[PDB]
Image (cartoon, rainbow, N blue to C red; front, side):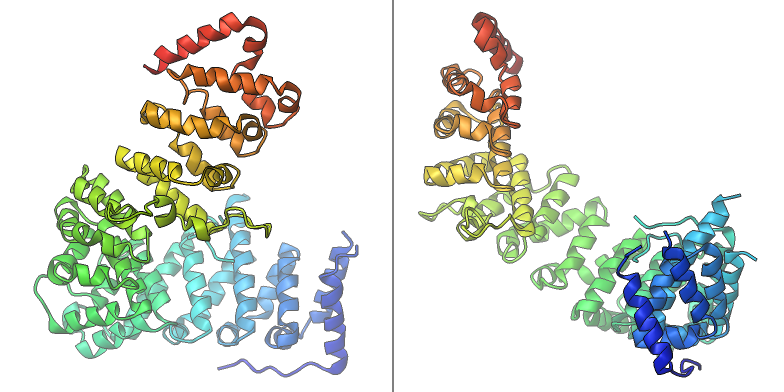
Length: 543
């Protein structure tokens, strides 16, 4: 109804363009004087400013950089056009900024005993008629989504969470229920609603702009309204197949927005409803859903997380036998199932193990490393010439592998043998690598590994004892070798000898001096007898 408030002069435009530059410069706490000089010049033009693209961001800065009593002064200058501003491409981000600062101010008033809270309530009240429109407006829907987060003390896009006053609870309710009316054009029962409006609503859940709002509400509505009638808007209560709901489900599953709406929603549904959906519609599509990764396999994860013993068992029964084909593109389906299998007391565990070994170590091959199955090793950052750090994905991969190791002895052995299968220098390379080294050291589970493998591993690493202990990463591999070497102490001797051979290189190596302590090399050097004691100590400390 109102978003075009005139334009700026050339003189005015120049002044502010000027102003904005010197602010992002920081050539100064006289900052303030400048800032509040801008404010004085902004006096009475706030609207033109906030709507113009050139100056839109200037305002946003001033909002971020001003007195609380200037904050309010600006907030005030927006009375009676808050709705227009939110519908504006630029003004609506100014609003987003302004409302977030206000939130903190309102927490402050809340903790630090005309108030910001009341200034706020006032604005909330002029939006109220316009909610329903705000919901599917490309810009205003965000301002709306924001507000709801604010009123519910949910962390704020813009670790940023503030405590709310009581009236905020009231106001959250007034806007949840105002929407409900706008969209059910009249109370008072699921009975009274046409499936003309029900489906009108179902169609929303798949809009890119309105679906996030509907999710938010559905999650947050529980605080007051135990109905939960927004959910019931979207879904039926019990306990039979409706071809309307059913085809709506498939409509959800056959869409990115729709699938993610679904899974987020599964998260805040009460368990009654989730089981219902599963029992009714999911149960016999569960594979087709899983292999429709993605999206649609995201949902099957949500089910697993948020369901109970009988159901998850049912699911695993369906999923484990196709796990090797399900790891195709995405590993994080695998961790889902393992976590699932475990949380249920190792249900279907062996076939799970069996399925992994199928995907990553199939005994029908020359090449067999999980090191190449699981980390794309040859294709990785392992020694690039180009000074490249490990990727986030590489870390992501490593971690996966690491828990595989934890999951079963089978996997620990398989990776050891994969490391052993490698050219030795390439295993050495691993030791100096940011994430991959952690994989090496993670393999050094002295109790879980048998001696022949231990001996063989030791043999590669001993060749580089000192270079290892003076490297940021290698030192951890060397540290663990102290225990890793119990009952194999012609190798302890070997290394200790090697390290003492290079005493001055090793101490006054940041990382070296540390290994020195842990191998107790100070003893070695002075009371060699007392050393050979410790070793015998640590043997029966382990066994």
